Length: 150
Length: 165
Image (cartoon, rainbow over all chains, first blue to last red; front, side):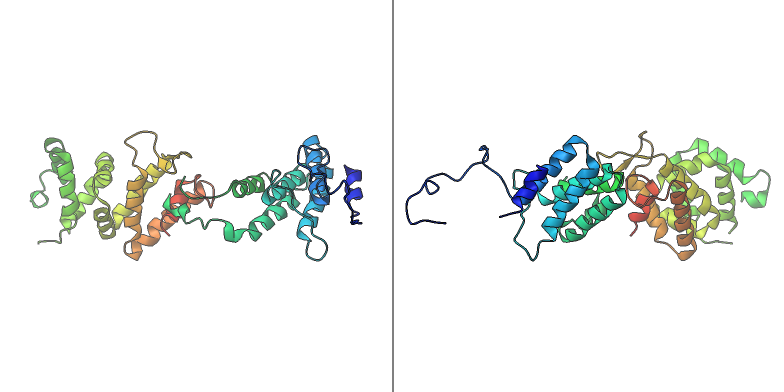
């Protein structure tokens, strides 16, 4: 996978009927489904965290978030596909990895940046006074949980 | 009449009264007698002493009456302020929080519920300033005593100070 990432870094239609025109676009079950650089750097980092090489997993996840959030100028690098994780779960896995690496002072600047950018989404905690009904997505609770363990 | 007589002490009279007749009625009465202006304040002055002598009644006193009445009582008689706060403080310290229902509760049934204790403190805080600073300081010192948390579920005293603003 390490090799594959460096591989995917690199990116004629004849007036005739060829095979490509007839071949179907591939599915997810296919072995020929290969996402983009970013969906695979996320595969690598996921498998790195699954294995217990968390120091390395931390570097990969900071390279992933660097791709996704330092994306203004170049060709776009997409977040993981929908069957994978949503974008707050990518920040959380990033924090978990840096925690196991012994870099807890960085997993706080991660979680704080996640709650900074989505403040406006978060509930105003006036229900805090009034105390099942109101709404909060799990990734917000989970961030306080990790910000604790940090 | 007993004071001018001076034969037996008022404490004896009050004790005898307390056994004979219905207690909750008597207590309601006492509250109001504690506030009537003099008609000659020796009347009230005797009862404060009798009450501070006998804790059990004052246990049922501050337990039975409503809030605003005890608030007016205490502002009238500063001698009643600190003990009453001790009574309330003691009822706070014998609650426990359960996480599933977002409410402080007591283990035993006769332990004052959250609502009543909130009521009394709200009445005490909505009072003249001679008592407001006293109760507020008595609460902060009991908060800091039990860990200076700033989030609910840990300290009854945090939840009170929050449910005031």
